[PDB]
Amino acid sequence: ATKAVCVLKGDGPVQGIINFEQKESNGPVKVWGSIKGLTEGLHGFHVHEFGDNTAGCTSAGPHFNPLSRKHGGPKDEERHVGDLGNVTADKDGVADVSIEDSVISLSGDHCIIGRTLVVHEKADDLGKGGNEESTKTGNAGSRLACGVIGIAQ
Amino acid sequence: ATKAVCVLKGDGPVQGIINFEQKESNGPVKVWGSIKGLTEGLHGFHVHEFGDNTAGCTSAGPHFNPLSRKHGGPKDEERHVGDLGNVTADKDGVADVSIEDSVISLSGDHCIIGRTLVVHEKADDLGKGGNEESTKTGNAGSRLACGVIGIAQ
Picture 1 (tube, one colour):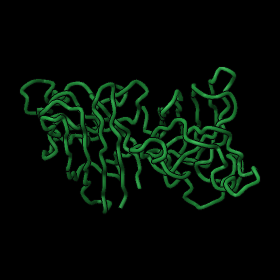
Picture 2 (cartoon, helix red, strand yellow):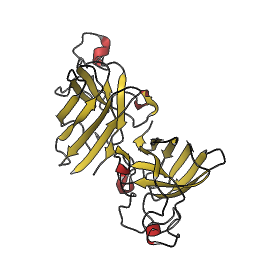
Picture 3 (cartoon, chains in turn purple, brown):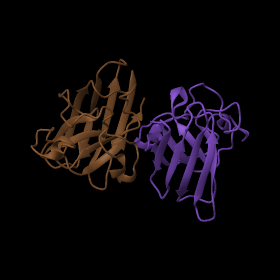
Picture 4 (cartoon, chains in turn yellow, brown):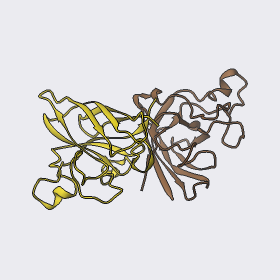
């Protein structure tokens, strides 16, 4: 699968479309789109383990972390597969997204298709926030918006 | 035993949770759950090719038919991978689903995780409708409600 897409929606105004492209199965995944509805500033941006929205975003569960590592930022060696850092919303609540990542995949064991992309309430402190929660979830707060990542044309 | 789940939703009152379970890679896929908000009677229940909701259910595209077969019913040899037949709404609009299918899969070429389950407007005529369309789509009409099939716990 070389393309994927996620429609983010949640209980308040957070909504967005995030596209994923991996033209090479052992290359990086391009991640791109916009999210609006957002308080200006930095927002956690993570792959959670499950594509389960039966009870809203809480259902997705934890980060996708198949290898059982500590939470870190996308550029760290010590991180979850799902740790994609923070997106930044401008003064207008619009976050334009442009990421490449070489940990997540569109195939194989690091495959995120069928899982959940979640935009969070506050900044992921990237494991450098000074408390025990930081090295688990990065303290990014609640789940504003989520959507199961799906195969795209 | 890999597991999957779809939360089905649309512009209307139709809402559902459909669950998937395949205890063996080659095993049959057991699919159970509920859908409410339906007119009494049968509605077509189809897996469509994409997990794309950028435009509502339309963007899921056509039935998932990797083998270029003709539309038929779940019990037919000539059918799409996606052709799961019809679910039945009681007169209170509730359709308790309990299917078992051996053409869909949670693994492999015929993997449906990341694609889109859809419940349609009308009965699927199962390719036995007597017109050109019957054998393309099954005359099931509009997509009432769909969800991306996601990995579940």
